Amino acid sequence: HDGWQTLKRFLPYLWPADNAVLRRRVVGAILMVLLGKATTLALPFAYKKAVDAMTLGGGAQPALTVALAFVLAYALGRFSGVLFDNLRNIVFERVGQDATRHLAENVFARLHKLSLRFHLARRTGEVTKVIERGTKSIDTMLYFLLFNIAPTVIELTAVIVIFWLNFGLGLVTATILAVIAYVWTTRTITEWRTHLREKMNRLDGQALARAVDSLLNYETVKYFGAESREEARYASAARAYADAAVKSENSLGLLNIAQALIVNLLMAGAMAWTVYGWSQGKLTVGDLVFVNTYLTQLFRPLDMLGMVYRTIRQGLIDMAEMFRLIDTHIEVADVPNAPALVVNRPSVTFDNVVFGYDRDREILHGLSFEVAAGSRVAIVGPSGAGKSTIARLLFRFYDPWEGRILIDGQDIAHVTQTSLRAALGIVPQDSVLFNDTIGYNIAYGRDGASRAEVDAAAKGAAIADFIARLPQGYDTEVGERGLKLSGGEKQRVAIARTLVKNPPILLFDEATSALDTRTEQDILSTMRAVASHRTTISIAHRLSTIADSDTILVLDQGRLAEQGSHLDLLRRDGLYAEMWARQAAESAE
Amino acid sequence: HDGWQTLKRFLPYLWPADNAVLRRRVVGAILMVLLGKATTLALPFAYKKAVDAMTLGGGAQPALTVALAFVLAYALGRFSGVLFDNLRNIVFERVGQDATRHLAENVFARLHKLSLRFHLARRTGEVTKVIERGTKSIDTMLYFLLFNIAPTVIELTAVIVIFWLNFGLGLVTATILAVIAYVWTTRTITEWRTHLREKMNRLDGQALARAVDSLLNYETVKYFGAESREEARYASAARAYADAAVKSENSLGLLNIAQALIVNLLMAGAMAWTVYGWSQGKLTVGDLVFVNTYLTQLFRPLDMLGMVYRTIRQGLIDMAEMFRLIDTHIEVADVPNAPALVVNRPSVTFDNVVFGYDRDREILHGLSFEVAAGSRVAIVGPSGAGKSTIARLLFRFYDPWEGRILIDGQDIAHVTQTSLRAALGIVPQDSVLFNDTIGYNIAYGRDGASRAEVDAAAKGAAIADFIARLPQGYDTEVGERGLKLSGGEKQRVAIARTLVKNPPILLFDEATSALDTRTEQDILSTMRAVASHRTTISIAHRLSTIADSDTILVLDQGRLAEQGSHLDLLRRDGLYAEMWARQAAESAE
């Protein structure tokens, strides 16, 4: 966390060396800065020459011409100064916005490329609040640091050197002492004011909370005649808040008093010195109005320094946070020169696969099997065998500790991630919808998803009647901030999403676990309809719902416990039959 | 909604005619206003006299003395101007706070004195947000209207008259044309800027929402490889937001450009005119620096006018709202010369009492009974007979349509409200707690509730063991933003509240309806313990819980349907026995 290395990391994001309009815009910005401060310091010189030409008219008879010219130059220079300041804002704001936009885009890209255990260790609300806080603080920090500190320090040093010329050292040390004591008392009294403002804010919150609670318990307040009690309570809270606000305004008043006091003492000293220097004939009358406009134009923008230090510290913190989110590497990555996963026979094999979510509790121990292509295979077990992890390890969200999963005899740990996630399909246990229209949710499965594929999936999931019954049809806004949908409808949406994706391999990760029995019995026929020519793996909780599979593999504590057809297991009369009778009695009860 | 009548109603709240420190403070405030503007307009006159005395030193040899004196007067006048402005803020802020505090206190008092159907027609959150919006908007409106508009209009008129003197009419019409065109272009371009800012705000909200939703659905986003899709989506939203922000800064830039342009054109014209007037010998050299400091001190505070109109309209709306909440009269009121309800024998009688909550559905029809003092009486019925209203009509929350309720043979519609609510006690169906400590909740029942009465109620409700088991004891913060309590505990708190109140008449308005059977069977013994020597009325839902009463009165559609003891009704074998067997079977099932 250092300003040097932090801003040096930021420096390519402002100076890209790739966009010529960007580098031209930033050099035009600093050009406008220097031009504005130059004309601002250069105008009162012309004003002094005007007053000198008007007062020494014994030698210069066309004082009309000379004074009129220098005076019009003064007015045009003032207008040009404000013109150049607003032009530097106009040229520079797009640069600032594009810098913070590229930084936000890059942290978003690195964030979405980051691995799943990052999104489980922290919360997505924390991440989005830190990035919006980052872009706001970086924008205001860049604006403040480049548009107050550099122009004020240029103006201050030029005023110091322009008083080193044309005047003695006494004016220079007087001005620099006034500047030092000014910024010192401003920083101290602003820290005191911020302390008072924090106290006033929390007292205000207490008063408002007392008010709303006393209003909300109106029935009991009537039940005990405590209206005078509650009025006195609210009055006490409001009185304390009023006294805190009065002390805050007292702090601001003392700030303005100190600032005006020190600047007027400096102005009195400088003007007395220059009128004495006129009296002993060294200095003309223009030097009075010279230092007069200099001081009143100098001491205005110096007030910001205390809040500038705070804002630049906050911007440094936020940029360090965004850069840390950049440099956080991914746990799972593709191998260098990753070949594409090629499928001709969508076969799965688990091979001695070892997994747990965390290293201190191993959940997957000894699974090794083969799922033939085109078949209907089934996974079931108790709540403690941990059947839910199989889809997440098949999608290469986590790599296994030991063992390997091969698709088509090829290591999915050794292929391209996008091809592996392309050849697969999943119905999640909890279906989720984007806050958008339903047609975009259906077309979400493929990037260039066509409308013919959209209503093809809508008839394939048997939801086309539901899209006909909607008022806006496919263009109905759904999800949050839209029309809520039922669970079976959402699962049909997920089925249509998978059919838009069209994989050879699909998975049901407890697709009916949160649904009712009617939607269940309706949806199993649909699942068999998608299960025409694909390799289908189904993990379920209610065995009757998977009673029709080709084979069932029953898992226990990370071991392939049982394997075989439903008739074979209900003839073997073991844990399968026990769970079956358990589910039968639990459904009968 | 007129400013005249609205502010004329507000005028006693600022000028109380009762607090001499308040009237002295407000007259000191306007004194400081006039003194500050007077010294601000009076200083550049002394500056002009200084420059004149320095330039005409052929006649005035002690130009040292004269110029030094007028210059030091100029600097001290500048400091005194800023001094008087901060003093007017210091003296006036307490006045503003006390005015809005008294208005807020009065609307709070009228609100709590208002009747119950007001709190059911509107929401308490709406009421508290309108009063906090009112006090904030009234404070900022009073501050803006009294501390910008009046000083700027005084300064503007004094500048106009001070240019009417010492100069021709041309300067006056030039300055007034510049002021008019200035405020005109400021109002127009500020309205345009506010339009752009609203568009930029809603676009920003859309971009942030897209970001957080794309982060939250991370699993499905990984499930379909749509990282590039979501990155392009977020980039598109951020790009549109950036363009909106650029257009907003363009609006602000054009505002500053127009303002600086018009003020510098006026300054160029005025200075050219006065240097020509010097050239033809009418005007001295001090008139240049005179008009020079006049214009740069004049045109700064004029920018606020467009937002001032908006803020004064909003303050007018909020003050009209607070005044409407004041003038809203109460539906139920005490009779003029209301005698105090006096109790020697706490007897109740209902007499042909007619009630409904609204006039289009009559709920109470023909109830007329007598509850003897010291007895244990019981009310029960179905869900549709409407038994819940009896406590609310006994507390005179609503008056009956026809008929009368007498306590001790006296009309409770004709006694003092505070004595009537003093002689009564209630356990509500839903217990509520203030966000405070538990000991204050126990002491809530009486205004001067002593600690001996507090632990007397705590042992009487059998909650003293629960107050011993608490870490902070009686001083434990409870409720919301504190330790949550269970339902039976909250009912015991309510019982202790009623015992602190100590009435001769108490009511149980479904005291066990939301409690479990164990807390119920524990709490009925406690209810019989409070039922020693008081007139007890109990309305219940589960008849076994009221199977021990002296008599039961069963209500049906606002009629006294059944009356008698439990043995008499279970021997009469009617609707009571049917409800009893219904509750027995519903408890067995």
Image: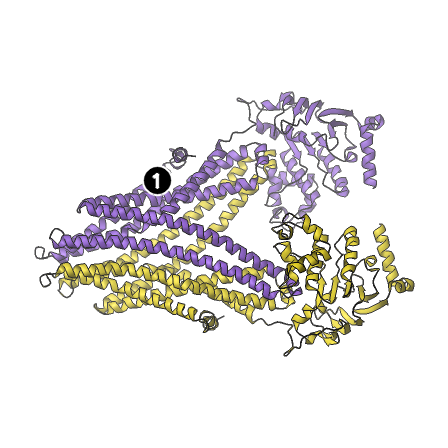
Chain colours: A purple, B yellow
Could you tell me residue B250's position as x and y percent?
Answer: 38, 50
Front position in the image: B376 or B214: B376
Residue B336 located left or right of residue B386: left
Residue B343 shows in this picture: yes
Q: Which residue is most to the bottom?
A: B337
Residue at (27, 57) in percent of width and height: B264
- The kind of secondary structure element at disc 1 is helix
Quadrant showing the N terminus of chain A: top left
Q: Quadrant of residue B566?
A: bottom right
> Badge 1: how crowded within 10 Å, few (<14), some, or many (20+)?
many
Would you name the residue on which mark 1 appears? A26
Residue A102 shows in this picture: no
Front position in the image: B78 or B535: B535
Could you tell me residue A466's position as x and y percent?
Answer: 69, 46
Label 1 amino acid?
Val
Residue at (67, 42) in percent of width and height: A490
